[PDB]
Image: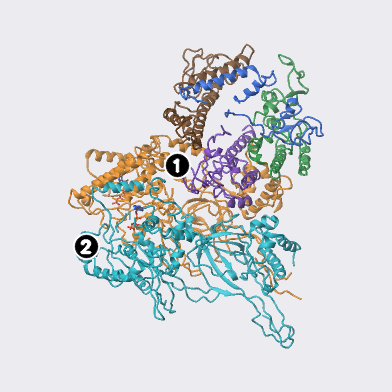
Chain colours: A blue, B green, C orange, D cyan, E purple, F brown
Amino acid sequence: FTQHILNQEESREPDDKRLSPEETKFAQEFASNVDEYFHKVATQYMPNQEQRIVTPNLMSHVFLKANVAVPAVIVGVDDEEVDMAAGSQHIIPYQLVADLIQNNQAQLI
Amino acid sequence: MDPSIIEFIGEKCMISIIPNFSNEPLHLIYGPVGPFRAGFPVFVPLWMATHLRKQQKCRIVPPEWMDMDILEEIKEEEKRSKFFTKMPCEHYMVVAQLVMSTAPDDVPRCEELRTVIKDIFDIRESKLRTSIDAFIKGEGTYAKLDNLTLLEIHSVRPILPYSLDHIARYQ
Amino acid sequence: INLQAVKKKYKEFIRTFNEENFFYKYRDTLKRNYLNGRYFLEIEMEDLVGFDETLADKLNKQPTEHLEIFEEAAREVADEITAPRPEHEEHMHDIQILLSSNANPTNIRQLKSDCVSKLVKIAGIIVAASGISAKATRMSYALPRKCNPKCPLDPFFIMPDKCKCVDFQTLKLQELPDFVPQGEIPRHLQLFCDRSLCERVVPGNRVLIQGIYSIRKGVRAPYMRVVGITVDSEGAGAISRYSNITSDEEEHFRRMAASGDIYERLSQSLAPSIFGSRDIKKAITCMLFGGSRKRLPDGLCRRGDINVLLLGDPGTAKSQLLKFVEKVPIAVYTSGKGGLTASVMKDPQTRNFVMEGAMVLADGGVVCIDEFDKMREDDRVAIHEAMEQQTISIAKAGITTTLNSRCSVLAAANSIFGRWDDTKGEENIDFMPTILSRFDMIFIVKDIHDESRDITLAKHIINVHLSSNKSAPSEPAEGEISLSTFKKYIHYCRTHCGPRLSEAAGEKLKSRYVLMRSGAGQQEKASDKRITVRQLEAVIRISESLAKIRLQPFATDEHVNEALRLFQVSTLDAAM
Amino acid sequence: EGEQFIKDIQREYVDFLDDEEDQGIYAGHVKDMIAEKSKRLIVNVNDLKRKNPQRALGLLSNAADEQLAFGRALKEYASTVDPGYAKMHEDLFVGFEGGNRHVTPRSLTSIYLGNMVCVEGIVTKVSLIRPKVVRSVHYCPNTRKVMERKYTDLTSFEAVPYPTKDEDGNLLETEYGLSVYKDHQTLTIQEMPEKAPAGQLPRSVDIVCDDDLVDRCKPGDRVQIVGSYRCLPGKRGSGTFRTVLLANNISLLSKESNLDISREDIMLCKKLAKNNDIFELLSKSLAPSIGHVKQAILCLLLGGVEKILPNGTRLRGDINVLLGDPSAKSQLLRYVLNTAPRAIPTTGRGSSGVGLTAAVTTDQETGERRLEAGAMVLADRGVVCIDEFDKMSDIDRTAIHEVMEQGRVTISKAGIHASLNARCSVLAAANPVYGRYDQYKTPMENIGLQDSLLSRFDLLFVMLDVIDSDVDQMISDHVVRMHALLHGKSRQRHEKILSVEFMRKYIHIAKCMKPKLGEQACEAIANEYSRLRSQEAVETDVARTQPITARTLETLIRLSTAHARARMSKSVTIDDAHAAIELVQ
Amino acid sequence: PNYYSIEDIFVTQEKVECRVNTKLQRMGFLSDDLEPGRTVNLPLWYIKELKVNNAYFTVAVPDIYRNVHKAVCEAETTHIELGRLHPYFYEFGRYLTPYDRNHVIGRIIFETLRQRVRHLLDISKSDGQAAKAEHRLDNIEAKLHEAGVRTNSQYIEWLQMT
Amino acid sequence: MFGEKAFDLLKELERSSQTIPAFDDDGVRQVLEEIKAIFEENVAQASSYNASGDRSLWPLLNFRHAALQRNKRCLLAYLYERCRRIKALRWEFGPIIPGDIKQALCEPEVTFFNNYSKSLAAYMCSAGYNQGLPIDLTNNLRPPKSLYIEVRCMEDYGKFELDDGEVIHLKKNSQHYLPRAQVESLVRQGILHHI
Ligand SMILES: Nc1ncnc2c1ncn2[C@@H]1O[C@H](COP(=O)(O)OP(=O)(O)OP(=O)(O)O)[C@@H](O)[C@H]1O
Ligand SMILES: Nc1ncnc2c1ncn2[C@@H]1O[C@H](COP(=O)(O)OP(=O)(O)OP(=O)(O)O)[C@@H](O)[C@H]1O
């Protein structure tokens, strides 16, 4: 995911929440290196004039563990997230829920 | 997902045994451990009974959910369990293997338990396919965990979803 | 008793099979058969001794009942595991069992009254067997009198909407050729097979068998069936259609393939007792491998395999070589005296004109013969035809079922007066050229003199012919070993690859054949007195065979310089 | 009336009758309102699954009486829609017509019992016919009440069933006329065998049929069928088991009328007919995989032309030819077996049934006395090929003389005088006595058979192979070309204007016309035959000019006729003369 | 520039049987002028971004892709058999769907692969030796096929210390 | 072939699983002699009056675009799988025992290789300790025991053990003055499934 991680980090460069600095050290090291290795392919005729992305997808179905109210604690998520529980799960994807986990309300396995 | 990765999870669980020593050249490690003196129980995790029983130091005994009778009535509860059944510690498919591997030099009834635990294992596993022969319409807000365990569910995890998302996108 | 068996023993037997490593069961095997529609299971006969010490000694005496107590135990132990919950046993289903052993094989000559209704083990050979009619279990033998105003004396209407159906095949067995047929001919026997083992044995194979010798009606009749067949390992006694080869075998195989010292290794493979004759031998092995049977949108199903020739003075070991080529996937051998007709006979039952059909029996195998010479021409024309189109036709009575068979062919010969013809001109064959033309190889044999060769062929043979020598020192040579490997290896290599040429091979081959035909025509004109598509369409098959060897699909003409320098032997042989 | 669900099933097949799709189309103007009266309605299972899946796959799992319920519902419907044609008071079986499970005759294997499924195989054993016994409107003059009694058997439905002295001893005049009858039939199928493993014998099946479906092809064609399974008799309750098939509509898979032939495809044909130099194309069409004939082999593929007189006699219209040392003559005949209809190779070594029968029977179920078939009537109105001719015996040759030349087969097998209509042509292959030879010794006597046949055939001819040192590189060029799409667009072509399928589809009209002779063939043919018999026997060719007769006329007219069919010019010209005759010279 | 995978470019190559509506110029890889109607094969890359409403080429489907088989195989979605005459058959519409003008194909595709949500009841094991059912395959279902075989083959190794 | 060969490009490493004899720099030479044969046409008509500004040239743009796509991404594979497998064995050892050859370094790969080595340098610096304790992480997993003895193994070559012994002959019978810091590299490269 060395491609558009950088877009969020230039959105704010978050604090200790999102990333750590040495990873950014690595990221710029690698992003420079691939180009200076591409050196000996096409750099006397490198491109003359967006589309290269790697890890964008946010719908890989995961398994949730709820940890909360045995009734349906309804929270910020797009679907009918009804029937939340204390020991149970109704499966969902990750786009609609990157919210509970940042609350540490819910868990994965 | 591995045969041992989840033992770096599951093997941390606790049992209670009796060692044969006094306190060791060091008596106790600063932590939840209790003091070491022969002839009496002590409560431990499971990354030592491996190390201990074959180090020819002590005995070992199991928890209570390992028996015949409880694991002969839980199955007939499971038969009508249209959803799920009773769950003794929820990663009990691995403590059994790491117990019945070494321990049986002294443990009682070290086969018929294997019989019943597999007899529950298979029935619940075959249950966990028939979710799929009814799972319709991309229903990715409705599914089952209610008294499920973990050591079965890695036996599905990389097959279905990794493709299910980018496939049943259409609905 | 009927139930104390199923009550606990068989029912818990499968449940109880336990070695840690958590494999040692027949439960998981049963389920992984079930999932894929197979409906069978295998066992040994000396594992029950690992469970008890009596039941086996009861299994031998009353097998026919025990082998149904098994089926009941099998399904009542398996449908519990069918149940995911009570909602996916759509309906139960029946199974058949297999048992095996390694005890000892017997011979047909001891199948007598005492060995009746009793388990056995034998080892024989097959000729042919029937088709697949039917048989079933129940529906809605004596069908007694009572009826169930009157309804008289056995009015029973079968309800075959409500009947059932299993299989029926009637296999066969002939003996082996080393158990006193010497002052006799070989007898044989007919058999019986039940549910899932039709299309398990084609005729022309070596068998192990587990069976039982039981009757149907004091001169009453014999028969036998399968009680859990298995097969033979005469090197690879039965490795002819299926695959219990494993990734280990594929690994060893393909690791042999890339080993680029295998072909010159294999030019010394056939004879651990014969000296010399290596250029003769570099393409007796490719004949097995075969090339490509490339059909096209038009008609041209062009000739797949290749064909062999040899004629020479005796004293150069022709016979042993051809017997060895028979020995090492499937093939048969006659020589002369046999056909031009095929088999339109008549079963005296029903009086029809059935077609019994034996170039049929090499449809993936091959055939070898000696003496095309000393068998006259009334039976050469059907074989004129077969080996160019393989559409073996029939037009005798009111049937025109031009069936077909893909076979190759190997030819030994004997010319009159030795090399008398072979020095001078046109007495190479005495008969005709269009079966000398319609072949590929052209390899003559001579026995010329030289004292060094004389003395060497002297001592080379003595150490061979002294006291059954080769126990120790044959395999200790480099790589000249294990025909069994060759059998299984071929039955891989022929049945995978679909090779064909490159670009660069085509022009070089065309120019080379051009020079060949031009040299022949110049020999015509440089003597003031006197080149088929077959020669090109055959020599291409040696490139086909070589690429088959190394498993590369595409092959080069520099790879094939060996092949064309083999064909050079033919060219400079028929030099005149 | 058995289990009560049967009537739910009746109304559930009525539940097909909702709205426009079946309540509008499938019932009404369907057979009797359109007045074809072919009782069998056309069913398609897919719509059934699309309406009633429990009643769709209930059928392809069981057929106890669902057919009968279909028929009951159909009569209940048509009795309302149009009772005038409701006077056929019988079962009125229907389609079940329409790849769920299409196993071979080799694999009708111990399951599918109680199912309705698909088979393929050979049209074979086109066999004997009989009628069937149904029900009869009996009568008694003493009492004058026309009673009734229906008769069954298992091959019609489940159950199993003449009256004399019925009530107490009164009269019984069994009244026919109002007693009815179906038509009945029995024959078999064989696996189209070339899917065989020739280490095994292709297996067989058994099929039975019924009334309005009877005897719908000739044995020697390819076919599809879709039918159900039944198995009656004893099986150690008394001795083992047997099979039979029913419940089907017929499907032949080698026709042209199967094609939706409107007035447009004929329009393309007749448009392109104006193109003149198409003969050289169609010659280069037949054998795209091989030098070398086929300009005329085409005419052999056009049958011929039949010419009769008032109440006199008739002639045979077709052509037969052949010419060569070994190495592309025994690979140019499989352009017939699987290019064009009714093509049957024969052996070169097969006796006793090229036209013989042997008439053998052995106590048939009925009284089958004596008959079998042959290998020419199979090829009526078409063609035959053979390989390895000269090695054939000198036994059956004279049968070839007769049935070729006389154009009728009027034979007897020692029991019965026989006559039929077989009007076909034939080929074979060729081999000289001594291998590679036709030129230095003589052209003739290198063949070695009677000089009567070249009258029966048409052509004394020649075929060889080699070249000198200049053109040898040219044959190298062509051989390397044989050994893509480039420069066969220098060959201005398309894979639809030159192909197999459209090429086949130019059969119908070229064989439906009758391109009569004008007059201007006459003086040409006469002067040319004059020159032919005069000076064909000089300048190195005296002995190769023996077999001329007055038979080159019927061949010439066959030829110009055929060539007049390949463009449908309902007339005949001098250009047709040249294109027809240049072969002979 | 794609949803990559190890099948990086088995992606935009699938050839079709597109028709012609009006004229073009200078076909290049195959006249700066042509007729209205001449059938021609075409790849998928350059056609990927030429404006479904715009009409150089026409409403155009292949014959296996033509609605007849595809309809009777959303009714024969029980044993529609594949082989290798069209090995991949699982995300073709994941470009090609909207270009019909008769909106048919997406529902077909989804039902077919919803049958794999119904199908792989059985494929749960490697019972023995090498290869079992290795030619009814799209080579995206082959991925998860090998994957499930792996997970079971290692889960086996779990089943004891084995 | 027209964009197929990368599956052929890794085939130098077809046998090189864990019994590897050696490795090479295959499949770049004629293949990037391509790219200077084609740029001529790819930028031939740039804003040209060659066609007077007309729509027809759109296949050419996408031709260039897809050509770049295939070329660059096969390059990413020939880079990344090499680095990744080498990264596996480079987790099985530091630059203590580098590759079998160091002759198949596709020349610019010095930067690539050594940068990843400095990936692990950063790893060591921050992880292990804040100052950086290079944290023994994937080899030499003996519980605390003796420091200096030798033992038996199974015939490895490459012979790069520069660590703290005079000459130890790192194969079967590398059986000589071996300290702990000498033998600090091996757990799995094909060596000590058997002491
Ligand atoms: N070149 C050889 N090297 C070693 N042994 C040989 C050789 N040639 C022949 N022999 C011995 O002689 C026997 C082979 O004779 P073979 O049966 O081939 O003669 P043949 O070819 O059948 O003669 P003919 O063709 O006239 O029947 C073998 O049993 C072998 O022991
Ligand atoms: N011009 C050609 N067209 C088609 N096939 C050719 C041509 N030239 C050579 N061949 C091939 O060469 C082989 C020639 O053998 P062919 O079948 O003609 O023998 P044959 O004429 O049947 O022999 P015989 O007449 O003695 O039975 C065939 O496989 C054929 O495909």
Horizontal side of residue D185 vs D461, given as left or right: right
- Are circles 1 and 2 on residues that touch, CB within 8 Å? no
Q: Amino acid at mark 2?
A: Thr
Residue E152 lies in what quarter of the image? top right
Q: Are marks 1 and 2 on the same chain?
A: no
Q: Is mark 2 within 8 Å of ligand 2?
A: no
**Up/down of E142 relative to D56, above or below:** above
Secondary structure under tag 1 reads loop
Query: For mark 1, what is the residue?
Result: E32
The chain to which mark 2 is attached is: D
**Up/down of A35 relative to C281, above or below:** above
Task: Give the farthest residue toward the bottom.
Answer: D142
Instruction: Count the marks.
Output: 2
The chain to which mark 1 is attached is: E
Q: Identify the disc placed on residue A90.
A: none
Residue D331 lies in what quarter of the image? bottom left
Give D356 or F19, whichever is nearer the viewer.
Answer: D356
Query: For mark 2, what is the residue?
Result: D442
Q: Is residue D318 visible?
A: yes
**Up/down of C449 relative to D523, above or below:** above
Residue F143, percent from left and from top: 61, 18
Residue C315, percent from left and from top: 28, 47
Q: Is residue E119 visible?
A: no
Horizontal side of residue B1 vs D417, given as left or right: right
Q: Amino acid at mark 1?
A: Asp
